């Protein structure tokens, strides 16, 4: 199609590997580019950890208010929110918000611990029908993004379908789904990625991710004005281990998709 020609040209100009999945919920059509190739998820995996904890709270109604102690030993490489609460507590709701809206890595590791390890996050993916997602490591090593390494990867198609189910579908209860949507809409890290390629009137909830090999990711639910929402996943990774992040590529991919 026309969009796939332009995405391939974008990819060629960028020097990396680009994966795109769009789901238009108006007619359940999909637009895929390398939709079935694995990409390192990096921090986009935090959506699955948060959703898994939300799913637990459908039975444990008070779970999100449970205080979790933040100790100096818990802090890893990037903890913008958790660092504000060292030797204090944060609730699981606060940790989920910090993981999603600030990409706090300590928050993610606490969510993983709550689920019983990376295997517990992966279990939740399987439970909602995602057989592709795999979380193998904790923060920060899940971001190594080594070419060919299947650990901590998913495919664009799988992540788009799962993000659709979590936010627009009914994989979560109604209160949990609304909470997830609210968190995603309040993301603070996404201004230069998918959002930058879309009309300013459209409301976006997204989760970015970045890692080694210049890995630059963004997954988003998009509510266009007077139009059915869209789910857009953009994964991008590069051949050089020290390559710089390329958020502009995600913005350009979104712009190409939005032209259609």
Image: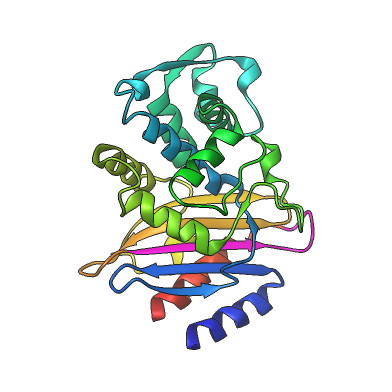
Q: How many marks?
A: 0
> Looking at the image, which is closer to me, 100 or 41?
41
Counting from the top left corner in percent of width and height, residue 54 is at 38, 34
The single residue placed furthest to the left in the displayed view is 226
Query: Can residue 191 be seen in this snapshot?
Result: no
Q: In the figure, 107 relative to 172: above or below?
A: above
Name the residue rendered at 51%, 59% in the picture: 158
Q: Verify whether residue 189 appears in magenta.
A: no
> Looking at the image, which is closer to me, 89 or 59?
59
Counting from the top left corner in percent of width and height, residue 31 is at 46, 75
Residues drawn in magenta: 230-243
Q: Verify whether residue 238 appears in magenta.
A: yes
Counting from the top left corner in percent of width and height, residue 58 is at 31, 31
Name the residue rendered at 49%, 83% in the picture: 3
Q: Answer with left or right where residue 110 lies relative to residue 95.
A: right
Query: Can residue 30 be seen in this snapshot?
Result: yes
Q: In the figure, 3 relative to 95: above or below?
A: below
Please name the colour scheme applied to the rendered image: rainbow
Name the residue rendered at 30%, 38% in the picture: 176
Name the residue rendered at 31%, 53% in the picture: 169
Counting from the top left corner in percent of width and height, residue 200 is at 33, 64
């Amino acid at each position: 199609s026309a969009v796939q020609q332009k995405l391939a040209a974008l990819e060629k100009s960028s020097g990396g590997r680009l994966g795109v999945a769009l789901i238009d919920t108006a007619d359940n059509t999909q637009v895929l580019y390398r939709g079935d190739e694995r990409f390192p998820m990096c921090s986009t995996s935090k959506v699955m950890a948060a959703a898994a904890v939300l799913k637990q709270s459908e039975t444990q109604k008070q779970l999100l208010n449970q205080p979790v102690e933040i100790k100096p030993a818990d802090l890893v490489n990037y903890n913008p929110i958790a660092e504000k609460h060292v030797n204090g507590t944060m609730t699981l709701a606060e940790l989920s918000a910090a993981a999603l809206q600030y990409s706090d890595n300590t928050a993610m590791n606490k969510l993983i611990a709550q689920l019983g390890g990376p295997g517990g996050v992966t279990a939740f993916a399987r439970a909602i029908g995602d057989e592709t997602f795999r979380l193998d490591r904790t923060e920060p090593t899940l971001n190594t993004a080594i070419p060919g390494d299947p650990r901590d990867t998913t495919t664009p198609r799988a992540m788009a379908q799962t993000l659709r189910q979590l936010t627009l579908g009914h994989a979560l209860g109604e209160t949990q789904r609304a909470q997830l949507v609210t968190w995603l809409k309040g993301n603070t890290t996404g201004a230069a990625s998918i959002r930058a390629g879309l009309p300013t009137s459209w409301t976006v909830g997204d989760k970015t991710g970045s890692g080694d090999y210049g890995t630059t990711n963004d997954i988003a639910v998009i509510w266009p004005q007077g139009r059915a929402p869209l789910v857009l996943v953009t994964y991008f990774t590069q051949p050089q281990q020290n390559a710089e992040s390329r958020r502009d590529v995600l913005a350009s991919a979104a712009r190409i998709i939005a032209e259609g």
